[PDB]
Length: 83
Length: 83
Image (cartoon, rainbow over all chains, first blue to last red; front, top):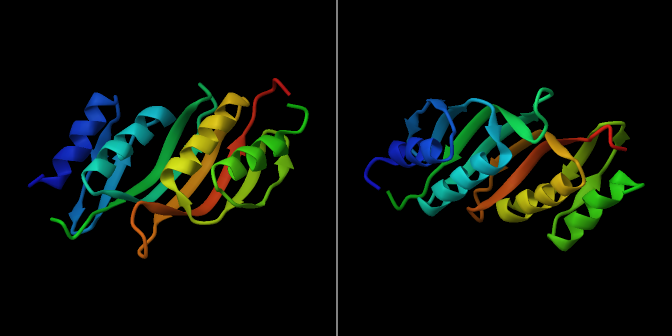
């Protein structure tokens, strides 16, 4: 993975996740993700986990309108020295 | 599930998660969970998800000492009117 930013939006899109903002700040990335399936956002990070990415920050809230969905307050990804 | 507090610690323990603090504040609960497998803490919430519990807040950070593990900053659970 030459472009770490890709895995996020790539895995995001396939999981129906909207990463509005991304920032390749070395290891840590700044991700902005609209309300999501707790499934999708996990599996997406699980997917990024394959990239050597760790959830460096995940900040989240349950939605009142459709329980079982979540609201990502702020999300930071961390990466390996691998790349 | 007459005692919602049980599912959390029950599912916690089976997933190797330490819920130090729990608060049955109606729908929302205050959970304090020591550093965890992102797998375990998800699967535990997935498990609580079976209880009718939503992750009302999940606040988390990646650990520097053993990547792929996470640090739960603050976690709030939300419950159904089912109980």
